[PDB]
Every structure is written in C-alpha cells, then in structure tokens.
Amino acid sequence: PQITLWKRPLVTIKIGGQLKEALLDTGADDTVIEEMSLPGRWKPKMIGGIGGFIKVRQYDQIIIEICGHKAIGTVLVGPTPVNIIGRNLLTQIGCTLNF
Amino acid sequence: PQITLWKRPLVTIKIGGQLKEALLDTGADDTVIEEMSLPGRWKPKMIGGIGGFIKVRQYDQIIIEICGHKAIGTVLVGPTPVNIIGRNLLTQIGCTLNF
Ligand SMILES: CSC[C@H](NC(=O)COc1cccc2cnccc12)C(=O)N[C@@H](Cc1ccccc1)[C@H](O)C(=O)N1CSC(C)(C)[C@H]1C(=O)N[C@H]1c2ccccc2C[C@H]1O
C-alpha cells in the first residue's frame, strides 16, 4: 500500500492478542506501546525525544502484525502518549519513504 | 528517491542559506529546528512528544530545501533534540510511506 501524510499514518496492529491503533513513525528508532502485558523477560530502558525521556520495559522477540504483515522484534512498553511503530519493525514489513 | 529505514532517515536541508542535517519524521505533525535566526514575526506554540511538551517559536512561510526539494511553510524553532522534518513539509515534497 501507499500511505500519504496529509494525516497521521495510523494503522491497526495486533500484539499480545490485542488490537491497538499505532502510528507508523520513521523518526522512532524503537517501537513503544502503552501499558499492556507481554510474555517473557524484560529489562528497563530510557527513551528520549521531544520533551525528554521516559522509562519503559524492553521485551525482546515479540511477534506483531502490522497492516496484515507479520514481524518479530523488540517492543518497549510504557507511558507513551501514542502507540508508535518504529524503524526496528518498519524495516521488517518493507516500509520505505518515497518522493 | 526511495529511503529505507535500516538507518535513521537523515537528510541535508537548506534553511537561511545554511546546510543542516534533519530527520524525515512521519510521526511528527510539524517541522522543528534547533535554535537559529529566522526572519519575520513568530507566534507561540506548544508541541508534545515522547517525554512531554516544549515551547517553540512558530515562523510561517519559510523557504526550506529538503534533499534538494524546495518547500515553503511553517518551521518551529526550539529545544528539539534533533532537527525534524514533519508531515507539514513531507507532504509538500510529495513524500509517502510504501510497503
Ligand atoms: C512536532 S514534534 C512533536 C511530535 N508530536 C506529534 O506530532 C503529535 O503528538 C501527539 C499526538 C497525539 C497526542 C499526544 C499527546 N501528548 C503528546 C503528544 C501527542 C513528536 O514528537 N512526534 C514523535 C512521535 C510521537 C508522536 C506522538 C506522541 C509522542 C511522540 C516523533 O515522530 C518522533 O518519533 N521523534 C521526535 S524527536 C525524535 C528523537 C526524532 C523522535 C523520538 O522521540 N524518537 C525516540 C523514540 C520514540 C519512540 C520509541 C523509541 C524512541 C527512541 C527515540 O528514537
């Protein structure tokens, strides 16, 4: 698909058996999701951007489905204002910028 | 061009006759640049990101080249961690997400 940028590029994702809305974000190194349960071990991480840093839990080898494309990667969970799909998963679904 | 996302999508921009590096950021509504001098009057704006909100100065109708493509539009100036080209200008240069 081709997604224009007149509005926020929001998509439905499936993660941890839950459906969520998330933003396809080429400015994010990592993927961060609002508070939810995920399986496995985690470790704490700080992530920073406009407004400063927040603390999140880092879960590895999590499967997500993003617009019908399956991928696996690290997912961070914490008090993000918006669910964000970052480059670590955008690459896996073959997402590129084109102009 | 087509820009893949295995690395940060950093590009060269030209603003105020000077070259700077900036990030193509589909997660950003607006374009925000580190402190610099821009002509004309500015208005106040608050923008919020992953760590909270910051105050910036809004300049309208600013000439800016992004990867050699000419745009003219709103540029915010303030304490951003990285120069960010947001959707207001990514649309001007005809940028889309594709997968
Ligand atoms: C014009 S700058 C402000 C911009 N915000 C927006 O466009 C819209 O914000 C909002 C929309 C809706 C509700 C909100 C509620 N509270 C606050 C903001 C809200 C923004 O910062 N967008 C960021 C994404 C975001 C969207 C909505 C809420 C919060 C964040 C941006 O696309 C990004 O990733 N940025 C801007 S600064 C940056 C470093 C280039 C990068 C970043 O934070 N990256 C970090 C990140 C993000 C997520 C996961 C990991 C990491 C590491 C690091 O890579």
Image (tube, coloured by chain):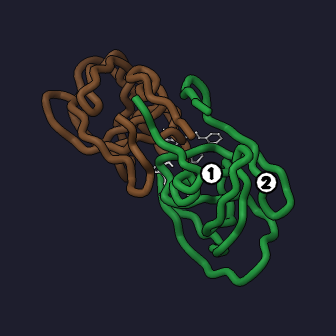
Chain colours: A green, B brown
* Location of residue B95 in the rendering, given as x and y in whole percent from the top left corner: 44, 28
Q: Mark 2 points at which residue?
A: A14
Confirm or reject: label 2 Cβ below 8 Å from ligand 1. no
Q: Nearer the viewer, residue B98 or B65?
A: B98
Query: In the rendered view, would you say A11 is above or below A71?
Result: above
Residue at 45 percent of width and 38 percent of height = A97
Q: Can residue A72 be seen in this view?
A: yes
Name the kind of residue labelled 1 in the image. Answer: Ile
Residue A84 numbered tag = 1
Q: Mark 1 lies on which chain?
A: A
Name the kind of residue labelled 2 in the image. Answer: Lys
Which class describes the residues within 10 Å of circle 2: few (<14), some (14-19), or many (20+)?
A: some
Image-based side of B46 in relation to A7, left or right:
left
Residue at 43 percent of width and 29 percent of height = B90
Element under disc 2: strand
Image label count: 2
Element under disc 1: strand
User: Which of disc 2 and disc 1 is earlier in sequence?
Assistant: 2
* Location of residue A15 in the rendering, given as x and y in whole percent from the top left corner: 78, 59
Image-based side of B78 in relation to A1, left or right:
left
* Co-location on one chain, circles 1 and 2: yes
Residue A4 numbered tag = none
Q: Which of A99 and B37 is in front in this view?
A: A99
Confirm or reject: label 1 Cβ below 8 Å from ligand 1. yes
* Location of residue B70 in the rendering, given as x and y in whole percent from the top left corner: 27, 20
* Location of residue B7 in the rendering, given as x and y in whole percent from the top left corner: 39, 56
Between the C-alphas of marks 1 and 2, the distance is 13 Å
Mark 1 or 2, closer to the camera: 2
Query: In the rendered view, would you say B36 is above or below A61?
Result: above
